[PDB]
Length: 285
Image (tube, rainbow, N blue to C red; front, side):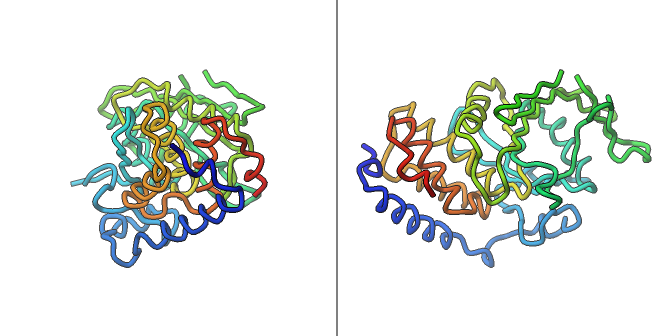
Protein backbone atom coordinates (compact mmCIF):
# COMPACT_ATOMS: atom_id res chain seq x y z
CA UNK A 1 0.00 0.00 0.00
CA UNK A 2 2.91 2.35 0.68
CA UNK A 3 5.65 1.55 -1.90
CA UNK A 4 8.00 4.07 -0.27
CA UNK A 5 8.42 1.68 2.66
CA UNK A 6 9.78 -1.05 0.37
CA UNK A 7 12.37 1.27 -1.23
CA UNK A 8 15.96 1.01 -0.02
CA UNK A 9 17.02 3.88 2.22
CA UNK A 10 19.20 5.30 -0.59
CA UNK A 11 16.28 5.06 -3.03
CA UNK A 12 13.94 6.66 -0.48
CA UNK A 13 16.20 9.66 -0.09
CA UNK A 14 16.80 9.91 -3.84
CA UNK A 15 13.03 9.66 -4.29
CA UNK A 16 12.31 12.36 -1.73
CA UNK A 17 14.94 14.54 -3.34
CA UNK A 18 13.60 14.41 -6.90
CA UNK A 19 10.05 14.65 -5.56
CA UNK A 20 11.00 17.83 -3.70
CA UNK A 21 12.78 19.42 -6.68
CA UNK A 22 9.56 18.88 -8.64
CA UNK A 23 7.47 20.32 -5.79
CA UNK A 24 9.73 23.38 -5.63
CA UNK A 25 9.27 24.29 -9.31
CA UNK A 26 5.57 23.49 -9.12
CA UNK A 27 4.71 27.10 -8.30
CA UNK A 28 6.08 30.06 -10.25
CA UNK A 29 6.54 32.97 -7.84
CA UNK A 30 6.41 35.65 -10.53
CA UNK A 31 3.00 34.37 -11.64
CA UNK A 32 0.94 34.68 -8.47
CA UNK A 33 -1.40 37.43 -7.32
CA UNK A 34 0.12 38.94 -4.17
CA UNK A 35 -1.89 42.17 -4.22
CA UNK A 36 -3.14 42.66 -0.66
CA UNK A 37 0.12 41.31 0.74
CA UNK A 38 2.06 43.85 -1.31
CA UNK A 39 -0.18 46.67 -0.12
CA UNK A 40 0.71 45.67 3.44
CA UNK A 41 4.48 45.67 2.99
CA UNK A 42 4.90 47.42 6.33
CA UNK A 43 3.27 44.51 8.17
CA UNK A 44 5.33 41.85 6.40
CA UNK A 45 8.21 40.27 8.29
CA UNK A 46 10.09 39.27 5.17
CA UNK A 47 10.36 41.00 1.79
CA UNK A 48 9.95 37.80 -0.25
CA UNK A 49 7.36 36.01 1.92
CA UNK A 50 3.91 36.97 0.70
CA UNK A 51 0.38 35.63 1.16
CA UNK A 52 -1.47 34.25 -1.88
CA UNK A 53 -4.47 36.41 -2.75
CA UNK A 54 -6.82 33.54 -3.59
CA UNK A 55 -6.53 31.94 -0.13
CA UNK A 56 -5.49 34.94 1.91
CA UNK A 57 -6.71 35.01 5.51
CA UNK A 58 -8.47 36.80 6.89
CA UNK A 59 -10.43 37.23 3.59
CA UNK A 60 -10.55 40.74 2.06
CA UNK A 61 -12.90 50.41 5.35
CA UNK A 62 -10.35 48.62 7.53
CA UNK A 63 -9.12 45.12 6.70
CA UNK A 64 -7.03 43.26 9.33
CA UNK A 65 -3.95 41.71 7.71
CA UNK A 66 -1.65 38.94 9.05
CA UNK A 67 0.16 37.61 5.98
CA UNK A 68 -1.69 34.34 6.38
CA UNK A 69 -3.50 31.80 4.27
CA UNK A 70 -6.41 29.45 4.79
CA UNK A 71 -5.26 25.86 4.42
CA UNK A 72 -8.30 23.65 3.91
CA UNK A 73 -7.47 20.07 2.86
CA UNK A 74 -10.91 18.64 3.64
CA UNK A 75 -10.04 17.30 7.08
CA UNK A 76 -11.73 17.55 10.49
CA UNK A 77 -9.64 20.71 10.90
CA UNK A 78 -8.81 23.65 8.65
CA UNK A 79 -5.70 25.77 9.30
CA UNK A 80 -4.36 29.27 9.05
CA UNK A 81 -0.68 29.50 8.11
CA UNK A 82 0.95 32.87 8.70
CA UNK A 83 4.18 34.60 9.71
CA UNK A 84 4.91 35.86 13.21
CA UNK A 85 3.24 39.31 13.40
CA UNK A 86 5.60 42.27 13.28
CA UNK A 87 4.99 44.93 15.98
CA UNK A 88 2.91 47.16 13.65
CA UNK A 89 0.83 44.05 12.87
CA UNK A 90 0.18 42.49 16.30
CA UNK A 91 -3.12 44.39 16.81
CA UNK A 92 -4.31 42.88 13.49
CA UNK A 93 -3.08 39.42 14.57
CA UNK A 94 -4.75 39.59 17.98
CA UNK A 95 -7.88 41.16 16.48
CA UNK A 96 -8.23 38.31 14.07
CA UNK A 97 -7.90 35.68 16.77
CA UNK A 98 -10.81 37.44 18.55
CA UNK A 99 -12.87 38.28 15.47
CA UNK A 100 -12.58 34.73 14.04
CA UNK A 101 -12.81 33.09 17.48
CA UNK A 102 -9.71 31.01 16.97
CA UNK A 103 -9.41 28.55 19.89
CA UNK A 104 -5.92 27.24 19.19
CA UNK A 105 -2.72 28.97 18.05
CA UNK A 106 0.45 26.93 17.44
CA UNK A 107 3.84 28.71 17.31
CA UNK A 108 6.81 26.76 15.91
CA UNK A 109 9.47 29.33 16.62
CA UNK A 110 11.45 31.09 19.31
CA UNK A 111 11.39 34.89 19.52
CA UNK A 112 15.10 34.77 18.53
CA UNK A 113 17.45 31.90 17.55
CA UNK A 114 20.79 32.92 18.77
CA UNK A 115 20.10 36.64 18.50
CA UNK A 116 18.47 36.48 15.09
CA UNK A 117 15.05 38.13 15.38
CA UNK A 118 12.32 35.67 14.42
CA UNK A 119 9.13 36.72 16.19
CA UNK A 120 7.47 39.30 18.39
CA UNK A 121 6.17 38.36 21.82
CA UNK A 122 2.40 38.87 22.17
CA UNK A 123 1.82 37.21 25.51
CA UNK A 124 2.42 38.48 29.03
CA UNK A 125 5.67 37.18 30.58
CA UNK A 126 6.83 37.02 34.18
CA UNK A 127 5.70 38.99 35.84
CA UNK A 128 3.12 40.83 33.80
CA UNK A 129 -0.59 40.06 33.76
CA UNK A 130 -1.43 42.31 30.86
CA UNK A 131 0.03 43.37 27.54
CA UNK A 132 -1.47 46.00 25.27
CA UNK A 133 -0.87 46.81 21.64
CA UNK A 134 0.08 49.52 21.15
CA UNK A 135 -0.52 50.65 24.79
CA UNK A 136 0.01 54.39 24.40
CA UNK A 137 -2.93 54.81 22.00
CA UNK A 138 -6.64 54.99 22.90
CA UNK A 139 -8.40 52.07 21.23
CA UNK A 140 -5.85 49.32 21.97
CA UNK A 141 -6.06 45.55 22.22
CA UNK A 142 -5.24 43.87 25.53
CA UNK A 143 -3.81 40.42 26.10
CA UNK A 144 -4.06 39.18 29.65
CA UNK A 145 -3.47 35.86 31.37
CA UNK A 146 -6.39 33.56 32.02
CA UNK A 147 -2.78 29.16 33.82
CA UNK A 148 0.49 28.53 31.91
CA UNK A 149 2.39 25.24 31.96
CA UNK A 150 5.88 24.30 30.80
CA UNK A 151 6.81 20.83 29.57
CA UNK A 152 10.55 21.05 29.95
CA UNK A 153 11.32 17.76 28.19
CA UNK A 154 9.20 18.39 25.12
CA UNK A 155 10.12 22.10 25.00
CA UNK A 156 6.44 23.02 24.78
CA UNK A 157 4.81 25.94 26.59
CA UNK A 158 1.03 26.25 26.85
CA UNK A 159 -0.26 29.80 27.38
CA UNK A 160 -3.97 30.28 27.97
CA UNK A 161 -4.61 33.90 27.04
CA UNK A 162 -7.43 36.41 26.92
CA UNK A 163 -7.72 38.96 24.11
CA UNK A 164 -9.76 42.10 24.79
CA UNK A 165 -10.80 43.98 21.64
CA UNK A 166 -12.49 47.32 22.40
CA UNK A 167 -16.23 47.04 21.79
CA UNK A 168 -16.17 43.26 21.82
CA UNK A 169 -16.42 40.39 24.32
CA UNK A 170 -13.31 38.75 25.80
CA UNK A 171 -11.93 35.91 23.70
CA UNK A 172 -9.93 33.13 25.25
CA UNK A 173 -7.39 31.38 23.09
CA UNK A 174 -4.75 28.79 23.88
CA UNK A 175 -1.32 29.23 22.35
CA UNK A 176 1.09 26.34 22.24
CA UNK A 177 4.74 27.24 21.55
CA UNK A 178 7.36 24.70 20.56
CA UNK A 179 10.94 25.91 20.87
CA UNK A 180 12.87 22.78 19.85
CA UNK A 181 12.39 23.48 16.14
CA UNK A 182 15.04 25.68 14.44
CA UNK A 183 14.20 27.77 11.40
CA UNK A 184 14.87 25.93 8.13
CA UNK A 185 15.36 22.81 10.26
CA UNK A 186 13.63 19.76 11.76
CA UNK A 187 12.05 18.95 15.16
CA UNK A 188 14.62 18.11 17.85
CA UNK A 189 12.53 15.20 19.19
CA UNK A 190 9.91 12.91 17.69
CA UNK A 191 7.93 13.02 20.93
CA UNK A 192 7.54 16.81 20.79
CA UNK A 193 6.39 16.57 17.17
CA UNK A 194 3.90 13.88 18.14
CA UNK A 195 2.57 15.86 21.07
CA UNK A 196 1.90 18.77 18.70
CA UNK A 197 0.06 16.57 16.24
CA UNK A 198 -1.90 15.16 19.16
CA UNK A 199 -2.80 18.61 20.44
CA UNK A 200 -4.13 19.51 16.99
CA UNK A 201 -6.13 16.29 16.53
CA UNK A 202 -7.68 16.45 20.00
CA UNK A 203 -8.81 20.09 19.67
CA UNK A 204 -12.56 20.67 19.59
CA UNK A 205 -13.21 23.77 17.50
CA UNK A 206 -15.35 25.18 14.71
CA UNK A 207 -12.72 27.76 13.78
CA UNK A 208 -9.44 27.27 11.89
CA UNK A 209 -6.45 26.30 13.94
CA UNK A 210 -3.82 28.95 13.44
CA UNK A 211 -0.26 27.77 12.98
CA UNK A 212 2.68 30.09 12.46
CA UNK A 213 6.36 30.19 12.82
CA UNK A 214 8.65 33.03 11.75
CA UNK A 215 7.79 33.16 8.05
CA UNK A 216 4.92 30.69 8.48
CA UNK A 217 5.99 28.37 5.64
CA UNK A 218 8.71 25.86 6.48
CA UNK A 219 7.89 24.39 9.89
CA UNK A 220 4.37 25.61 9.48
CA UNK A 221 3.73 23.54 6.37
CA UNK A 222 5.70 20.58 7.72
CA UNK A 223 3.38 20.31 10.77
CA UNK A 224 0.18 20.80 8.80
CA UNK A 225 1.40 18.30 6.21
CA UNK A 226 2.21 15.67 8.87
CA UNK A 227 -1.24 16.09 10.46
CA UNK A 228 -2.89 15.58 7.07
CA UNK A 229 -0.96 12.45 6.15
CA UNK A 230 -1.66 10.84 9.54
CA UNK A 231 -5.31 11.59 8.98
CA UNK A 232 -5.15 9.76 5.61
CA UNK A 233 -3.59 6.82 7.47
CA UNK A 234 -6.34 6.69 10.12
CA UNK A 235 -8.96 6.82 7.35
CA UNK A 236 -7.33 3.87 5.58
CA UNK A 237 -6.83 5.98 2.46
CA UNK A 238 -3.01 6.08 2.37
CA UNK A 239 -1.74 6.04 -1.23
CA UNK A 240 1.72 6.09 -2.87
CA UNK A 241 1.39 9.78 -3.74
CA UNK A 242 -0.34 10.85 -0.50
CA UNK A 243 2.56 12.86 0.95
CA UNK A 244 3.41 14.33 -2.42
CA UNK A 245 -0.10 15.64 -3.08
CA UNK A 246 -0.61 16.96 0.43
CA UNK A 247 2.49 19.05 0.02
CA UNK A 248 1.56 20.07 -3.55
CA UNK A 249 -1.86 21.21 -2.36
CA UNK A 250 -0.23 23.17 0.46
CA UNK A 251 2.23 24.92 -1.85
CA UNK A 252 -0.71 25.85 -4.08
CA UNK A 253 -2.50 27.54 -1.17
CA UNK A 254 0.48 29.38 0.29
CA UNK A 255 3.67 29.76 -1.74
CA UNK A 256 6.62 28.00 -0.08
CA UNK A 257 4.91 25.64 2.36
CA UNK A 258 7.71 23.24 3.39
CA UNK A 259 11.07 24.88 2.67
CA UNK A 260 13.65 22.12 2.85
CA UNK A 261 14.13 18.57 1.67
CA UNK A 262 14.79 17.67 5.30
CA UNK A 263 11.40 19.05 6.32
CA UNK A 264 9.72 17.18 3.49
CA UNK A 265 11.42 14.08 4.86
CA UNK A 266 9.91 14.61 8.32
CA UNK A 267 6.42 14.22 6.81
CA UNK A 268 7.37 10.92 5.15
CA UNK A 269 9.00 9.75 8.33
CA UNK A 270 5.86 10.53 10.29
CA UNK A 271 3.92 8.35 7.85
CA UNK A 272 6.45 5.51 7.73
CA UNK A 273 6.78 5.66 11.51
CA UNK A 274 3.04 5.25 12.11
CA UNK A 275 3.08 2.22 9.82
CA UNK A 276 5.71 0.65 12.08
CA UNK A 277 8.57 1.15 9.60
CA UNK A 278 12.09 1.60 11.05
CA UNK A 279 13.18 5.21 10.66
CA UNK A 280 16.80 5.04 11.88
CA UNK A 281 17.94 4.12 8.39
CA UNK A 282 17.04 7.50 6.93
CA UNK A 283 16.78 9.79 9.98
CA UNK A 284 20.55 9.71 9.75
CA UNK A 285 20.21 12.66 7.37
